[PDB]
Image: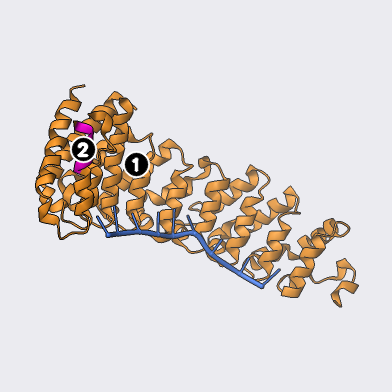
RNA sequence: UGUAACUUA
């Protein structure tokens, strides 16, 4: 427009950056190789004291993002030096979060990375603010970006926030928080996973039937480098309430996941002889529990799924040393008992499926 | 017969 007639050194780069027309003008000027280095250097010096302002700006953030693909190391470094103590405010912000992710995505070196982490430390960001960011609509996308871009050696402030008091509940039982927590465990180190796994088990009753928390428990059941400890821990914490948990909407999926995990281990043998022997002892104990409460499980709206999972011969066909003996005496007993209970559930819409699972047991037995 | 969660002209 009338702007594109003035020399670049006479542009008020602040007023343009906060203006839609002006911001688009500067971006497409950075994309002009003749002007690129010059506008950048002319832009950088004038907007330098307004970095935080531009970052949180509806139009300014678009310039900052674009500017990240052109800055030098020293330039981007000095940018981060100016704004690192304000990362919480930035991450919370609708526009700031888009800027910080792009900054994190275009880091040049550890000096820049450590400055960002330094801002997330307790010196500038309290634990309750980190917890906030994890559960925040916008901030959680910054925590994720850290989780995917930076190395786990930098995850300190995140780990510290989760293991603090009962924050594991606040996070796991939250829509945004449960996601980030699963994103973390996917790249975390084993010792960091343990540190979190302790807090989860400690607050297990508050997570296992939670609408989101149950997904955290199930995610832990996929981490193979946990079976040596997690199988005994859970079952010892849930055995007495195993029937109750099987009849709940959310925790029943965990039970099914648990049972399936027990099968895939003992079937793989035919992990570790400590894990396996424990898996066998739990499974046998589980079948004992399901026989005692068979009357209730077969009729419950959620219990029946766990019962079917346990009765599905598709999961334990190779089980047909001495363990396999008293297994069949228990799982076989449970089959013939379920067979007697069939006409007492004819009013239910799932009697057909259960009757078929005792039919599949005969096809494999005889 | 039964659950997800993961964002600006």
Quarter-wise, where is residue A225 in the image?
A: top left
Q: Residue A361's mark?
A: 2
Q: Nearer the viewer, residue A22 or A269?
A: A269
Task: Chain B: give its colour.
Answer: blue
Q: Which residue in the protein does label 1 denote?
A: A221
Q: Which residues are magenta?
A: A358-365
Q: CA distance from mark 2 to mark 1?
A: 27 Å
What residue is at 51 percent from the left and 41 percent from the top? A152
Q: Nearer the viewer, residue A10 or A269?
A: A269
**Crowd tier of the residue under label 2, counting other residues whose Cα lies within 10 Å: few below 14, some 14–19, many 20 or above:** many
Chain coloured orange in the rendered structure: A
Element under label 2? helix
Residue A137, x across and y down, in percent: 48, 64
Residue A167, x across and y down, in percent: 36, 54
> Along the horizontal axis of the image, is A343 left or right of A32?
left
Residue A29, x across and y down, in percent: 82, 63
N-terminal of the pair, mark 2 or mark 1, is 1
The answer to whether residue A72 is visible is: yes
What residue is at 16 percent from the left and 26 percent from the top? A325
A345 in relation to A261, above or below = below
């Amino acid at each position: 427009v009338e702007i594109s007639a003035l020399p670049l050194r006479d542009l008020d780069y602040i007023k343009l950056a906060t203006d839609q027309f002006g911001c688009r003008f500067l971006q497409k000027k950075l994309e002009t190789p003749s002007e690129s280095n010059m506008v950048r250097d002319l832009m950088y010096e004038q907007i330098k004291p307004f970095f935080l302002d531009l970052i949180l700006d509806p139009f300014g953030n678009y310039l900052v993002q674009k500017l990240c693909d052109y800055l030098t190391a020293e330039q981007k470094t000095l940018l981060i030096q100016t704004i690192y103590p304000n990362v919480f405010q930035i991450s919370i912000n609708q526009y700031g979060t888009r800027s910080l992710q792009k900054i994190i995505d275009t880091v040049d070196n550890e000096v820049q990375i450590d400055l960002i982490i330094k801002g997330f430390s307790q010196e500038f960001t309290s634990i309750e603010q980190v917890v906030t960011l994890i559960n925040d609509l916008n901030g959680n996308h910054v925590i994720q970006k850290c989780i995917f871009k930076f190395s786990p050696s930098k995850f300190g402030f995140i780990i510290d926030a989760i293991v603090e008091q009962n924050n594991i509940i606040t996070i796991s039982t939250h829509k945004h928080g449960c996601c980030v927590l699963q994103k973390l465990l996917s790249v975390c180190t084993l010792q960091q996973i343990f540190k979190i796994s302790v807090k989860i088990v400690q607050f297990l009753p508050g997570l296992i039937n939670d609408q989101f928390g149950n997904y955290i428990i199930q995610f832990l059941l996929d981490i193979k480098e946990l079976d040596f400890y997690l199988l005994a821990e859970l079952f010892n914490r849930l055995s007495n309430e195993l029937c109750q948990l099987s009849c709940l909407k959310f925790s029943s999926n965990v039970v099914e996941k648990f049972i399936k995990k027990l099968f895939r281990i003992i079937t793989g043998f035919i992990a570790s002889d400590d894990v396996i022997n424990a898996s066998m002892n739990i499974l046998l104990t589980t079948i004992d529990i399901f026989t005692v409460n068979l009357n209730v499980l077969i009729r419950d709206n959620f219990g029946n799924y766990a019962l079917q999972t346990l009765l599905d011969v598709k999961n334990y066909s190779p089980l047909l040393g001495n363990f396999c003996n008293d297994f069949s005496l228990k799982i076989g007993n449970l089959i013939v008992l379920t067979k007697e209970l069939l006409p007492s559930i004819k009013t239910t819409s799932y009697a057909k499926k259960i009757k078929l699972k005792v039919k599949a047991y005969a096809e494999a037995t005889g």
